Image 1 (tube, rainbow over the protein chains, first blue to last red):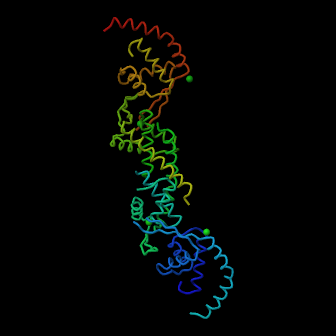
Image 2: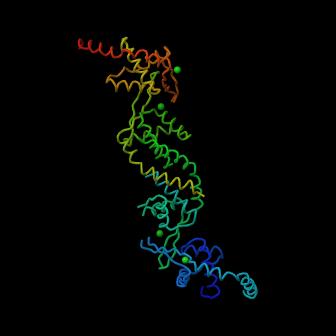
Image 3: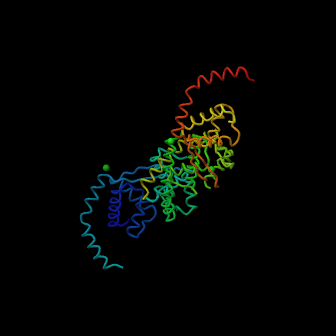
Amino acid sequence: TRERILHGLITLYILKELVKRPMHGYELQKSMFETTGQALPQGSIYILLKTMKERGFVISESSVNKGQQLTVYHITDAGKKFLCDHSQALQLARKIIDDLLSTVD
Amino acid sequence: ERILHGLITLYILKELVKRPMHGYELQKSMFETTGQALPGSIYILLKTMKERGFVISESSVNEKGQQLTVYHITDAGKKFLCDHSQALQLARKIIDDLLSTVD
Amino acid sequence: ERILHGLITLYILKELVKRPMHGYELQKSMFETTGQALPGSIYILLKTMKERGFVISESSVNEKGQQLTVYHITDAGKKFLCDHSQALQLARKIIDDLLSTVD
Amino acid sequence: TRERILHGLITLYILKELVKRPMHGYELQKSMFETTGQALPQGSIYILLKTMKERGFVISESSVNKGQQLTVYHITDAGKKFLCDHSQALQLARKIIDDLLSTVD
Ligand SMILES: [Cl-]
Ligand SMILES: [Cl-]
Ligand SMILES: [Cl-]
Ligand SMILES: [Cl-]
């Protein structure tokens, strides 16, 4: 998440998931894992979400249960626009990545 | 109450088929459905269910570094729920009778 | 099954409010209502109910000089049945949910 | 039941009860008891019912449970006629009984 291209892509993935329905962080973390076979480090999902909230892409809503915080994330209309805008050149991206991949262990 | 205990167990199982859930969520959805609000009762039932091999749980860290629990249905649990279809149908019949005729 | 056991107990109580009955009659009326036909199960439940102070029984000689048993509800039994009204309503809600959504 | 006037009256009572719904013997025995405060001797109800069946006033239907006989009695149309016929002078009967009663301990 600490690399720009990846940070961008993960943002998009989140956004796309949230279009489906609002989600907890743990759900986003799990789906991503299941989709790609790769797990984000503990707590890292929430840092990205924080950023997205700051950016205006997501709104959070928190409950408290033992006095623990249960937060669900919601995509904004702006977040939907960003997703839309930034998903237009994904085919080209994939082609480029493939090429690059042929050069990397 | 034995009747409600059984029914609530099944409701939880049905919820967990949908997707894994926190306790709090189960509690909330139930009240949505029931207008009914349960006394740590939920957690107690969940423990029993885990004892029975129907549910499993794992910890998940949250935004504040707090360890939250998420519950999952097992295959055993699924079958158990599935197995109770006819029992549910019968139960419905009895309740209808009761509600219509208790005098 | 805990759910059905409770429900059948209540059904019996409701029947006995109507008038005292033989076991066989309870068995028959249930199948009418349930299309459901119980395994000496009826007698077993009735014994428990008597243990609980909900039902009493007496012997009655028949046409052949055979001693038949007739079951009666007590006041305790009546209250017990009455007391379960809200539990029944809730149960109905849960069942409806289950039946509509189990997937 | 071993006295004519009483045997007649009890017959009528049975008939009247059966007009309500079919009944077991034990039910007839109980209702009578509750109504009058007086209990027929054991088994005696069934002897009277036998007679009524023979007379065409009642039809019986038996089940078996432990292999015991469970019988329900049903009034016939003839039984209903007899009831009707024989219940027309009951007021006069009551007046006479009252008078008689004034002479008996
Ligand atoms: Cl919005
Ligand atoms: Cl929780
Ligand atoms: Cl019986
Ligand atoms: Cl007839």
